[PDB]
């Protein structure tokens, strides 16, 4: 959780909407969005 201590990462996934400090991190993350289709309780 976050309230107001640090800033906000520039890169932000589009599939789920996550955030990443470094681009590379995202490029690799986006991959995870290549199967998970079924529902998920949070
Ligand atoms: Zn994502």
Image (tube, rainbow, N blue to C red):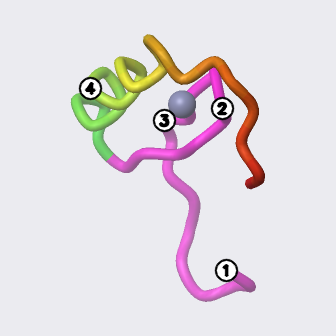
Q: Mark 1 or 3, which is nearer the eye?
A: 1
The residue that disc 4 covers is 28
Which quadrant is home to the N terminus?
Answer: bottom right
Classify mark 4: helix, strand or loop. Answer: helix
Cα distance, mark 4 to mark 1?
Answer: 24 Å
Q: At x 57% / y 59%, what residue is drawn?
A: 8
State which region is magenta. 1-21
31 part of magenta stretch:
no
Is residue 36 shown above or below 20? above
**Quarter assignment of residue 17:** top right
Q: Main secondary structure of the magenta part?
A: loop
Which is nearer the N-term, disc 4 or disc 1? 1
Which is nearer the N-term, disc 4 or disc 2? 2
Q: Give 41 or 16, whichever is nearer the viewer.
A: 41
Classify mark 2: helix, strand or loop. Answer: loop
Cα distance, mark 4 to mark 3?
Answer: 12 Å
Cα distance, mark 4 to mark 2?
Answer: 14 Å
The residue that disc 1 covers is 2
Percent x, y for residue 10?
Answer: 51, 41
Q: Is residue 11 left or right of residue 5?
A: left
Label 4 crowd bin: few (<14), some (14–19), many (20+), radius 10 Å: few
Which is nearer the N-term, disc 2 or disc 1? 1
CB at mark 2 closer than 8 A to ligand 1? yes
Which is nearer the N-term, disc 4 or disc 3? 3
Which quadrant is home to the C terminus?
Answer: bottom right
The residue that disc 3 covers is 11
The residue that disc 2 covers is 16
Q: Are marks 3 and 2 in contact (CB under 8 Å)?
A: no
Q: Of all residues shown, which one is farthest toward the front?
A: 38
Classify mark 1: helix, strand or loop. Answer: loop
């Amino acid at each position: 959780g976050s309230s107001g201590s640090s800033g906000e990462k520039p890169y932000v996934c589009s599939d789920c909407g996550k955030a990443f400090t470094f681009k590379s991190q995202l490029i690799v993350h986006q991959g995870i969005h290549t199967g998970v289709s079924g529902p998920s309780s949070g």
